[PDB]
């Protein structure tokens, strides 16, 4: 497949190769804060990242992934809407060419400059490939980015980007602490949805934090210097790698906070 974010291979085209793009539980969505329902039944959300073991950072020609050792329970997400234990496998971002766009989820139709996705899979399914074939296989923690003050926890990501400028490049990325990417509050919205890139599988419990993190102009500008293209190919800046909001259809968004 040769999908991307351009006029000729972007989100409006994806359904031809991935028909589930027009499915019943696609992501992202607009979070209407006035129709989301406070759910007192939600258990506390547990983000347990103290033993996280990062391995590598990779430019895959769509975004960049920071990958983790997910062979044991070293960084896991529990509680909230989740049953069982979800292992952190990777995180990546979606971002814009301008500060007023870039996020995939929106909040009362507001776009943020970027959105961080921490991707976790349900350990009952044994491996990530099996998990994505299950309706409760993944839990993605989504965190909005707005431009303001710098995020210190993000700088080590920023400073390795020059070494993975183009599609296919990877670099060592050990000893990175993903706790440094979290806002103060873990208040969240949650709903059942999908991957937001092909194959768009409907396997995700989305947990989207209410509180954005702030990153600096310089930090987001360095995201925008990445390339979609491979080395030696005509330069196409890696910007606007976000899917827009999809129809909510038969879904309720629940909130953890009143
Ligand atoms: C089956 O291959 C996969 C490709 C992408 C993904 C993810 C995690 C996509 C996304 O972030 O939307 C999962 C599996
Ligand atoms: Zn994503």
Image (cartoon, rainbow, N blue to C red):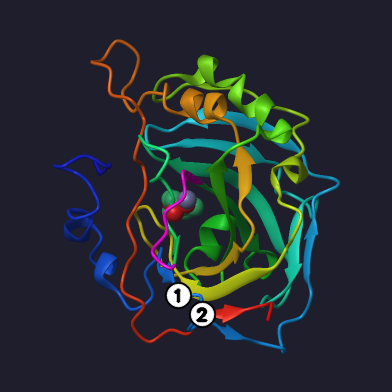
> Is 205 included in the stretch rendered in magenta?
no
Left or right side of 21 for 77 = right
Part of the protein shown in magenta: 108-114
The residue carrying mark 1 is: 32
Left or right side of 240 for 129 = right
Q: In the orientation shown, which residue stands out farthest toward the top? A: 232
Q: Overall secondary structure of the magenta stretch?
A: loop
In the displayed structure, 195 sits above or below 49; it is below
In the displayed structure, 233 sits above or below 142; it is above
What x and y, as percent, mark residue 211? 64, 58
What x and y, as percent, mark residue 91? 59, 45
Q: In the orientation shown, which residue stands out farthest toward the right? A: 50
Q: In the orientation shown, which residue stands out farthest toward the front? A: 148
What x and y, as percent, mark residue 219? 56, 27
Q: Residue at x 15, y 42 (%)?
A: 7
The residue nearer to you, when weighing 214 against 95, is 214
Label 1 crowding class (10 Å Cα cut-off): few <14, some 14-19, many 20+? Answer: few
What x and y, as percent, mark residue 156? 68, 25
Q: Residue at x 73, y 63 (%)?
A: 186
Left or right side of 237 for 76 = right
The residue carrying mark 2 is: 253
User: Distance between the Cα atoms at labels 1 and 2?
Assistant: 8 Å
The quarter in which the C terminus is drawn is bottom right
Answer whether labels 1 and 2 touch (C-beta < 8 Å): yes
Q: Which mark is residue 99?
A: none
Q: Which callout, 1 or 2, points at the residue further toward the start of the chain?
A: 1
* Mark 2: secondary structure: loop
Q: Residue at x 64, y 47 (%)?
A: 213
């Amino acid at each position: 497949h040769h999908w991307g974010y351009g006029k000729h291979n972007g989100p409006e085209h994806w359904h031809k190769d991935f028909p589930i793009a027009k499915g019943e539980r696609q992501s992202p969505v607009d979070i209407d804060t006035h129709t989301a329902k406070y759910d007192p039944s939600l258990k506390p959300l547990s983000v347990s990242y103290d033993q996280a073991t990062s391995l590598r950072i990779l430019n895959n020609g769509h975004a960049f992934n920071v990958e983790f050792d997910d062979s044991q329970d070293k960084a896991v997400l529990k509680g909230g809407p989740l049953d069982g234990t979800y292992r952190l496998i990777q995180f990546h971002f979606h971002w814009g060419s301008l500060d007023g766009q870039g996020s995939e989820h929106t909040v009362d139709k507001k776009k943020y400059a970027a959105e961080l996705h921490l991707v976790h899979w349900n350990t009952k399914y044994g491996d990530f490939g099996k998990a994505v074939q299950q309706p409760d296989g993944l839990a993605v923690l989504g965190i909005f980015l707005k431009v303001g003050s710098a995020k210190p926890g993000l700088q080590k990501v920023v400073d390795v980007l020059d070494s993975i400028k183009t599609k296919g490049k990877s670099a060592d990325f050990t000893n990175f602490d993903p706790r440094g990417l979290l806002p103060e509050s873990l208040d969240y919205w949650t709903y059942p949805g999908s991957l937001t890139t092909p194959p768009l599988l409907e396997c995700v419990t989305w947990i989207v934090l209410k509180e954005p993190i702030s990153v600096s102009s310089e930090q987001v500008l360095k995201f925008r210097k990445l390339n979609f293209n491979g080395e030696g190919e005509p330069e196409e800046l890696m910007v606007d790698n976000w899917r827009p909001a999809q129809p909510l259809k038969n879904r309720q968004i629940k909130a953890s906070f009143k």
